[PDB]
Image (spheres, coloured by chain):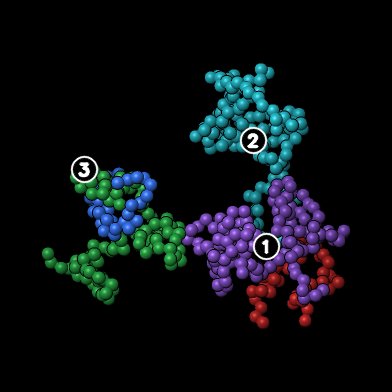
Amino acid sequence: NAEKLVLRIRIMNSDENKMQEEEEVVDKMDDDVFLRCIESNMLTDMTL
Amino acid sequence: GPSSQNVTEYVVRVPKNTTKKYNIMAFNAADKVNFATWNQARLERDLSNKPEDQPWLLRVNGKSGRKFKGIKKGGVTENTSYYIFTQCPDGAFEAFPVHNWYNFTPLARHRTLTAEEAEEEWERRNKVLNHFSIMQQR
Amino acid sequence: KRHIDQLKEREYNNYSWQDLVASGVVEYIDTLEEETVMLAMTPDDLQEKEVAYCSTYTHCEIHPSMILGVCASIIPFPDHNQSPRNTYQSAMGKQAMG
Amino acid sequence: MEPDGTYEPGFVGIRFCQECNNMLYPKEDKENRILLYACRNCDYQQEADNSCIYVNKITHEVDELTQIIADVSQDPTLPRTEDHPCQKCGHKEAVFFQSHSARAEDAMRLYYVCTAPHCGHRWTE
Amino acid sequence: YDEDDDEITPDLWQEACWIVISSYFDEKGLVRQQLDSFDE
Ligand SMILES: [Zn+2]
Ligand SMILES: [Zn+2]
């Protein structure tokens, strides 16, 4: 019933070890890029 | 003002000879270079090509104070000659021929990414995720 | 119409087609130019204003028969005839003895 | 907050790096809790002018009313209309057409451009 | 006549173009183009 249908999402950063816990100089995943990987995946993969 | 009122007339000469060849040295306006900051300059033909065709190498304020590379334009008198017009104390104008056009551009200092030690290989593995760390490892 | 009389003068004296080209009353035209020109079918009817849906015409055909080839030019009123028969004639004309 | 507003934030497609004219890239300052923009090849970096850094799925607007200089009006093969008043200049000779493109425009509706000097206006009715 | 002011034959006749047509073939010919490629 709103002015427009919008859906805003977040990654579930579960407080604990998801905070540079073991370094692993790899950068497990940058945020910015990860929003794009999900969105790339979100549009292209999911069949509702 | 005089830009909107003054009316003058001056004589023009085109001498069949000069004591020095005249060239154009062009800069990008977007850089807005302060020529006052140029305490000194060195100017030499570029060494990559190892003469008259050689691109210029301009070193201002020392070897690494400021450095530009000048690349010759394709043509300068292919259809129309270019002249330098200079004002003389007698008010008369003097015209000088443009021999050549060189394009001058700015040049980053020390940085050095080899892109040959393993970076050509690393690209094959690249996930676009890192780039800084290789620069420290050198 | 006087230029026609010049064309008539050419039978004896001279008035070259090139001069007609030099006259610039006609020009030679490619398909790229055709995309931009407003071509006319006929001088007569199209110059009429009474029913001028358009009058922005830029050029006109010499004659619609100019589309035709050597073979099609032989058979009269091809449009009162079924179209392939003409292609068959165009082939068969080539097949004729003479 | 009402179903009568619109979303024209004026997205910032790009900003060149003053050190190299290369594109600046978003980044967070998790220490200052602020968005920043940086170039990769150099150390040049600068704060962001807005929280919005991205937009997606396009073309739901009237493109055909844009990207059309009135100079089309000089084409004689484009029909004038007897319909007067250049939405600006009090003169007829409005040039008209559909969208005539890719969306080729199921919109078969005429779009009007006056050809009269001193207006250049592109509209439709 | 030519007064260089008006067209005295706005009904320039359809048949005159045939005078124009014969003049085309009189100059240009038919297979002329084939020679032109070879000649240049
Ligand atoms: Zn930069
Ligand atoms: Zn107008």
Dot 1 falls on a residue whose secondary structure is loop
Cα–Cα gap, marks 3 and 1: 84 Å
Location of mark 3 (residue): C13
Q: Amino acid at mark 1?
A: Lys
Q: Report the chain shown in green.
A: C
Q: Amino acid at mark 2?
A: Ala
How would you rate the neighbour count of disc 3 (Cα within 10 Å): few for under 14, some for 14-19, many for 20 or more?
Answer: few
Q: Within 8 Å of ligand 2, the CB of disc 3?
A: no
Residue B7: image quadrant is top right
Q: Which mark is residue B26?
A: 2
Residue C82, horizontal then vertical, whole percent: 27, 76
Q: Residue at x 23, y 62 (%)?
A: C70
Q: Report the chain shown in blue.
A: E
Residue C9, horizontal then vertical, whole percent: 23, 46
Q: Amino acid at mark 3?
A: Asn
Closest to the observer: C12 or D70? C12
